[PDB]
Image (cartoon, coloured by chain):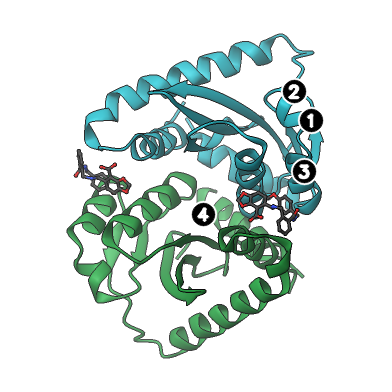
Chain colours: A green, B cyan
Amino acid sequence: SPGIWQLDCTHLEGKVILVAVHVASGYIEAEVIPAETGQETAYFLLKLAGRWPVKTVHTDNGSNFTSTTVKAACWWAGIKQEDGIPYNPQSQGVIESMNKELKKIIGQVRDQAEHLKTAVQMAVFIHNHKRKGYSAGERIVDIIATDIQ
Amino acid sequence: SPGIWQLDCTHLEGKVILVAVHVASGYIEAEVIPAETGQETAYFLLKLAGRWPVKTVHTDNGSNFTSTTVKAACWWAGIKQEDGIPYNPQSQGVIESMNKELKKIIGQVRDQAEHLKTAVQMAVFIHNHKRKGYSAGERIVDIIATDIQ
Ligand SMILES: COc1ccc(CNC(=O)c2ccccc2C[NH2+]Cc2ccc3c(c2C(=O)O)OCO3)cc1
Ligand SMILES: COc1ccc(CNC(=O)c2ccccc2C[NH2+]Cc2ccc3c(c2C(=O)O)OCO3)cc1
């Protein structure tokens, strides 16, 4: 479970916010793209896996699961590409709640930047730093370090 | 030391590669931009600090140190903005060698992608995963986890 991530795609302002969630910690990375394509998804995963030890990615939909470009990125970066079937129904709810939380934070910061991408990065920062007492950023580091040791 | 990062700007193919190095571990993040501007530098730091606990950034040059936009990003993200003066002469050499290493890796992957940004992200991946035996990615997580505990 330390290497397991979940992709998630949500929409705002006629743009697409692509999110990767570290399942065990709730830590996220995100980017704004014009539309979700295999190319954009592939590039995003390449970035993610250069930054964290990404063992498994549960793709967000069937198009990204199918995409040869996404498969090729997963091959390049040594990621096991998996489906995103919520065999645990709690998964849908957690992701939906996360999207609602992120959009709420974006709303709270929206007037602090012209561009949506800026507001999204502010939202990533707030989400990852929020104490719930550890933060998601603390949990991911602890989980991974424990795994290394 | 767990929170100290160094910015570094290098050039390839008429483009700019902006790098942040975690000093204690050698772990890096990087992006390709058309030109180094305070706006691009500010956005890069906002991204970095949402992902890792960035306490201090040694800026790469005086323009980024002076930049009101960079100062504002550092304010937003709770980062201490500092100069990049190599009071330790070993600093320059480490960065120089890092730039040379990165450009070597980019050359080794260059035909595996059309776009430079892709090759740069491949180089980030290879750099961070390289065992020197622990990798830079392992070292940063251990350093930060130790600090949290
Ligand atoms: C990350 O650095 C920051 C610097 C300053 C602030 C405080 N907020 C303002 O000063 C502000 C507020 C509203 C509109 C425009 C602005 C000025 N522009 C901020 C900005 C900077 C870099 C970028 C951007 C934007 C953007 O407006 O989207 O887009 C990609 O790179 C936040 C973040
Ligand atoms: C990250 O996913 C990967 C998928 C596949 C491969 C293996 N290499 C090739 O198939 C290849 C080789 C040479 C030229 C063009 C290509 C095909 N395009 C690769 C590509 C994908 C996503 C992107 C890109 C690019 C790019 O070419 O720069 O730019 C931003 O998003 C590597 C990484």
Amino acid type at mark 2: Gly
**What amino acid is labelled 1 in the image?**
Thr
- Give SS at disc 3: loop
Q: Residues within 10 Å of mark 2 (few under 14, many from 20)?
A: few
Numbered tag placed on residue B62 in the rendering: 2
Q: Is mark 1 within 8 Å of ligand 1?
A: no
Between marks 3 and 4 in the image, the one whose residue lies nearer the viewer: 3
Q: In the structure shown, which secondary structural element does the residue marked by tag 4 occupy? A: helix
Name the quadrant of the N terminus of chain B.
Answer: top right
Residue of label 1: B66
Q: What amino acid is found at the position of numbered circle 4 in the picture? A: Asp
Residue B124 at x, y = what percent? 44, 36
**Cα distance in 3D space between marks 3 and 1:** 19 Å
The image shows residue A59, relative to residue B61, as above or below, that is: below
Mark toward the start of the polypeptide (2 vs 3): 3
At horizontal 55% and vertical 14% (from top left) the residue drawn is B96
Amino acid type assigned to the residue bearing label 3 in the image:
Lys
Question: Are callouts 3 and 1 both on one chain?
Answer: yes
**Residues under labels 3 and 4: Cα distance?**
25 Å
Label 4 sits on residue: A147
**Residue for point 70% across, 65% down:** A126
Residue extending furthest toward the front: A114
Say which quarter of the image contains residue A27. Answer: bottom right
> Considering depth in this image, is B22 or B20 the residue closer to the camera?
B20
Question: Which residue in the structure is indicated by mark 3?
Answer: B55
Residue at disc 2, secondary structure: helix
Q: Relative to B10, is A102 on the left or the right?
A: right
Q: Earlier in the sequence, mark 3 or mark 1?
A: 3
Residue B141 in view here: yes
The response on whether ligand 1 sits within 8 Å of label 2 is no
The location of residue A108, given as percent across then percent down, is 72, 74
The front one of B94 and B64 is: B64
